[PDB]
Image (spheres, coloured by chain):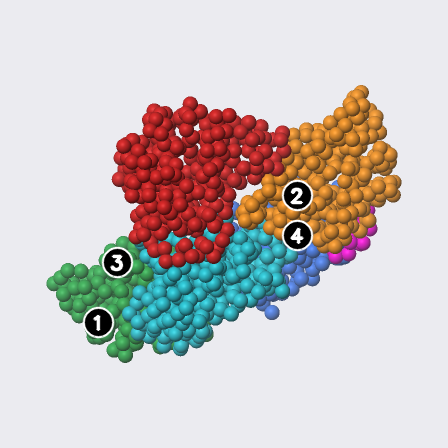
Chain colours: A red, B cyan, C orange, D blue, E green
Amino acid sequence: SPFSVKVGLAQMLRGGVIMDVVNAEQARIAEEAGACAVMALERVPADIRAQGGVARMSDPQMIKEIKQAVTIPVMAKARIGHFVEAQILEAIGIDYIDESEVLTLADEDHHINKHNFRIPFVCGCRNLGEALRRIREGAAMIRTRGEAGTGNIIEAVRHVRSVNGDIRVLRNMDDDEVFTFAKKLAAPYDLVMQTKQLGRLPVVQFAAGGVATPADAALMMQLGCDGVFVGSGIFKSGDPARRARAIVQAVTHYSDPEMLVEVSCGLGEA
Amino acid sequence: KSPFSVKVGLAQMLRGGVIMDVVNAEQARIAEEAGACAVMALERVPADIRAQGGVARMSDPQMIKEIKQAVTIPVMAKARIGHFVEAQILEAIGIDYIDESEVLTLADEDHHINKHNFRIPFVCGCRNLGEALRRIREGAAMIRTRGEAGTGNIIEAVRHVRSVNGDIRVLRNMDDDEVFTFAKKLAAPYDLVMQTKQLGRLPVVQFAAGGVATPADAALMMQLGCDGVFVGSGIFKSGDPARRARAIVQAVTHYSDPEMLVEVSCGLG
Amino acid sequence: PFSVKVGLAQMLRGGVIMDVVNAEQARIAEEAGACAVMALERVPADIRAQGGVARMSDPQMIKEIKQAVTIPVMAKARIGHFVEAQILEAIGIDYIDESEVLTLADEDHHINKHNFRIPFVCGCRNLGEALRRIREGAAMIRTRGEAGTGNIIEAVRHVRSVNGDIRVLRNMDDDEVFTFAKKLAAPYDLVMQTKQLGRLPVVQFAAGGVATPADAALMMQLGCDGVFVGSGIFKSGDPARRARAIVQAVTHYSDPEMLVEVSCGLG
Amino acid sequence: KSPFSVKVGLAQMLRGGVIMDVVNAEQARIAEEAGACAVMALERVPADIRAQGGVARMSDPQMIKEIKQAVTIPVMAKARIGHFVEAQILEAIGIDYIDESEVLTLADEDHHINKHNFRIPFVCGCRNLGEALRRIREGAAMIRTRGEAGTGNIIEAVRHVRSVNGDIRVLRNMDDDEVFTFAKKLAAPYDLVMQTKQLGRLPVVQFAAGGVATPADAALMMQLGCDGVFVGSGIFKSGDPARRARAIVQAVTHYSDPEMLVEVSC
Amino acid sequence: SPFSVKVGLAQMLRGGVIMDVVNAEQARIAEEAGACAVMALERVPADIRAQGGVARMSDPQMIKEIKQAVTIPVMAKARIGHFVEAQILEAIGIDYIDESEVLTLADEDHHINKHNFRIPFVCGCRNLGEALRRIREGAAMIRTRGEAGTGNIIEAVRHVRSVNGDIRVLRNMDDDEVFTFAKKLAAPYDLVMQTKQLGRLPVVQFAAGGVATPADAALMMQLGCDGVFVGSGIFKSGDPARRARAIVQAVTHYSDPEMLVEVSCGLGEA
């Protein structure tokens, strides 16, 4: 009912690219390049790993600057388990909250109870069980955690293959054996049977962590992802507008090699 | 007959050849002039990949096309292991051969590209016979021994060449009844193992790669049963690249002629 | 040709094969509607117990059973004992069982079954094991189960393992089947054949611990094409009746009313 | 013709043969009559050695002489491994072959008899090629695969035969440059390894021993590349020993003829 | 036959000192000081350990410069297992090839098949079995590997004592027990019996690795060595001619303490 409408809200981002932006200049460039949403944060994931320090929810002032600078949906990060950082973001009037593992963990044992919010949440996962548990907690959209800040697609591929692999195993599986499968996944049985009946994840599945090139973006789409997230890697190059446009084109035309060649050609240093 | 057999055939044309890593057109011309049978186009060398660290991907199509238009010999380029889209892009640029390379950052830890789904032929690495047979069944048209790229040290290449050729020779004479268990222990497809037994060699062209630094190295690989060698930027990181290039070509052509090896090695710095 | 031997074995689909130690027992098994009999001198329950080495049976006793019935006759060769197989081929039996219930004769190699004109049965515990036996030329696979115990638990584990992995395979990304063949240690061409068919490229029966009609029927409902049954049948009061019951159970495996009638008063 | 080559030659005459364990003259006559190419004289069988326990030595020369005078086919007897004096005694009784046997109680854990110091030829056991080559260099004229005596179980004999013949085949095709390291890993004398490469087989007669109980067993050994088989008192622990004996001889003679194997096995 | 003549060639160096030389200046000094042979290489063993990098066969140009600069035999190094580096050296017309462990190993499992060459090889060893295996592969001369580049005689003494120790054990050994001794050494039985009958190594045995002083050289000779190798240690001093002459004199007069005092006196820093 109110969950299905949050699920529905996130289906509108299918075939899209979401871009990390630290200011309004960057948010405009991302919108202009055809990003389906922007992710507002103050310190990038590559400079969070490197500089160290504690990474929290961004200053509401800077989030509001980005929300008023574009007409596409705006997302922002709450530390895992930080249900009050989420309450604040809901109250600023952003479109989506990302319960992010790129920020400093705030509860080691419990995630936000996402059903208690009106606006939809994105959660990370590395396997099907992790995704189903986030969904039952009320996540409306799943991303594969991948390995943020590296530019290395290897973990994203492992995770996407893990999730889609286990979904395919489910489809043909003897019904009598799905009980034990739900135990081994540590996932709620009703959401596992829903996943069997759909033959896919009961919500939008995007790829995140290490998508650096058009070819990366397209690979994720060909593996069965519904869209991709991309870091500030884009804006740490010579012509950010061009690199941004390239990844959008790549996700739109993911099965067209001729298109991938044209956008990749002369694209510089990643 | 089959589209695979045609790709295997295409790769036989490189037998007795030297393939050279080139980062620009200047280098590609030198390699062609020195008698290289093909060039391998990449932006960052394997010795500077190990050193600088960072993620190593497929090269910019712009620079690959510059090298393709600068020579008439075949051009190869690297796709990260399992990165089937980097391969699609390279197929579409119109290069001759794709190298599914372990010199680049791994992109799938568990799966290699399904190489049968491509029109142009692939090179794959291996360290033993089972690894080579698995790459072939995935559709590799040409195998190289992974060796140990960026070091200048032939020791790993020798281990691997000896491992592969060693196991091929064991196979040739092996009781047929025992080849089933041999296929299990190799974790290799039984039909390609029996094909290898019947031929008494690898069902595709086998080159050596990783640590071939000197003419003597190149010739050693050929005397161990390799069909050709790959060579890194080591060539172009010396005083007279033209000369060092020419020397390794001559060494692979005249691998059983000590008198020739002395002449090309003499004053090589 | 292999496909001819595969085809020969499809004729046993929906059948019960019965261990028999003499002609009296072979006639009872045929009369009860067994689709084949398995000739041996010492049963698997008395092999575990008496100890000692268990070999191919005396050709004299096998020939007595072959001349006593018109249904196919099977006999056991020790694993890897290709000469015990040559002898059985030459006696004119229909099927050779390369059996793990006999004393192993080669720890590292199975018979090269392609070098024989008559078809072979082989055991397995998982898909990889079955595919390897098939490529060696097995025309029919049984799940090894746990012979001599009367305990169905291992047969269920193995049937579920094989059918489970076949189902996983059907829906599996083609690009991932290479690595799947590596992890199974199975020949890639037979794995892709199994994917295309959506089942085992030969007849799959259950063996080891099938003691009751309910056991037989459970095997059939799990996706087996038939069952083997030991001398357990003939170690009871009315062997004819217990034999008939298991045949009926395999024929009518989805009919609870039938299973009640044959199980009732079975002692 | 070296004195070793003559002993090697003597043993080649047993090619295609069956050697039978016999505890008396009655049994020795039956074995000769059934077409055994030699008899092996001992007091306690290997199946009753494992069971009764105790120390197993060279047999009483009296009983060996009774068997030697009872047949015209060669007679063999067992010396404990390393017991060079038990060998001296057997040489002096005038038997044809000495078996340096692991079925008897070991007498030297670290050294085998120096078999070159004897006029008559020796049989030695092995489990792999290196072990065989080392026995040969010590002067063994004939090798048997140790198998697993007293059990009736062919499994160890098959493992060992496959091991030896397997390594011989690996050798045939092997790069010459790599044979040095192969000799190191086998712990075998390099000259005998190169001899084995050049012949494509064992430089002496190779028989199978330990667990050959049935005609099918005997024939399997022959099809795996053995030149003959040894057989225990298993034969004489049956109803008609003459018939079971004759069957194994027929099986080794006609090892690639299934129709023959069926008739003798029935 | 052709092996015995290579063995014979190397017997001519008995009582000699072989000197590592990196140029013709050094080769002349070594010849003048009475060296029985020179060993031609580009990078010394002390600077190979320190600078790191891969150490290969030297440039044939520099080897030929040294061969034409002296009338005493010239040796050069081939990496272990590098049979083509050996073919090249044979073809330059040097007198001896050293299959050296001071260079980067090129085959971990196999040494050069030295019988396939016309000119004689030197090989290293640390024990008798290792020496016998090199000899059977066709080595005409053995050196004890010692510990090259250190100036420390300790490993050379360990190895010389190990080899000569096992040769002495062999001499008195029951013939019946030599079979098992050959197994434990992992050495070819025929070469072990040859060693028993001679009461020494069937080829010339020199000491190498850590011979820095006249006293070192003499100690090696008194332990039963037939000669010594010496590194560039000699040429890394004030008067190379003098230090060179001293070690030659020491090996010639190894049982004359009065001679050892005179050559050692005022010899400076090693």
Which corner quadrant of the image does residue C203 belong to? Answer: top right
Report crowding for label 2: few under 14, some 14 to 19, many 20 or more residues within 10 A (C-alpha). Answer: some
Q: Which mark is residue D60?
A: none
Q: Report the chain holding disc 3.
A: E
Instruction: Tell me which residue sits at (70%, 47%) in the image.
Output: C138
User: Which-is-in-front pick, marks 2 and 3?
Assistant: 2
Say what amino acid the circle numbered 2 marks: Gly
Residue B41 magenta-highlighted:
no
Q: Kindly identify which residue carries mark 4.
A: D208
Judged from the image, the secondary structure of the residue bearing numbered disc 2 is loop
Cα gap from disc 4 to disc 1, whole angstroms: 66 Å
The percent coordinates of residue C263 (x first, y second) are 78, 24
- Which residue is found at the position 68% from the left and 38% from the top? C143
Q: Residue D264 colored magenta?
A: yes
Q: CA distance from mark 2 to mark 3?
A: 62 Å
- Residue underneath mark 1: E26
Left or right, C242 with respect to C45, comes to right
Which numbered disc, 4 or 1, marks the residue closer to the eye? 1
Q: Of E171 and E35, which appears nearest the observer?
A: E35
Query: Overall secondary structure of the magenta stretch?
Result: helix
